[PDB]
Image (cartoon, rainbow, N blue to C red):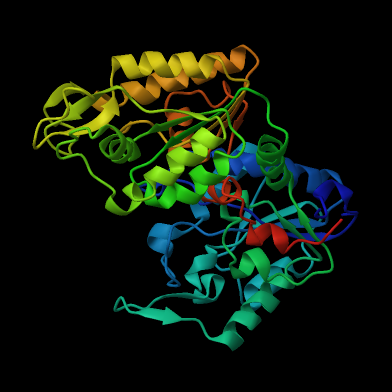
Length: 413
């Protein structure tokens, strides 16, 4: 119910656009430009529809309100965006100030400007830490001035930062312009999770993986009201198996608080006719390390003392392939094992292979932009699944039934 980019008359209008360019870095080098390319459509549309200019703003990492250009500058992003668009990008050393205001005041037609990390100013998040490491709160007056400054950089506001949509930060909800519309990425992201949560294909399978059960209670609960199947993998599994099967999980991390809610979780699944699938076997390590001694175990055998399950085993993989194959809609959020470590990545790799084939057979596959998105890029399956979200935290909120502050701040249709 929000104003969309394609419905705005951008003819000769300066466009101030919030995007999520917080991409994984390494030695000032980008290791994944997905979030960058994801914003291109909105940017191109603006320029192709007569926009006088397009000012881009985003955060990078967590500078906590302290200018750290030596390790958190968006300059590397400006260079990457320039190569992807084959069009010059004016990178400003800041996001506020007389210099920035002048540079965006009335740029030459077709100008693409990229501001510096918004989190170099405490006013963006509203809080942070000083040089000594002490948490500080931004001054109310400063926050208002910061938002008033950013608003002057454009005549029309566009928010395409789906990845940050869950953050009610200044650049996300404080821009005061007559028109505030969603970008192409923002709406594409929203529509996917909308249809999946309102008019889902069936069978409907949800794949949830994570270390703790506590932080996924509301997620699980909401999902059990619409899905037909649900696979729980990752560390959460050991909490369920221990409480439900009285399995000996050895040194496997246990979620004492999450286990208390396991009962009611299984009750709702039963009442909604949702078949929950847990692993039946696993790959163990004699310690929490990539080079740990590798072992094996089943529910019956349990896991030896001092050892922990870090991935599901061969029989579990076979079972997941069976459930994945009988689905027409799949929502995947969270790997099934420690994918970063080869010895415990087989489980997640197999699941990925099955999800890719599921797509080939006509299944709608939606991946939560998080660790699952990392896996897609890692194994090059980004173009083999229906949708790979650019925001894990944002999608999490949506799949929980919560609204996104970055969305609610936009103009209505």
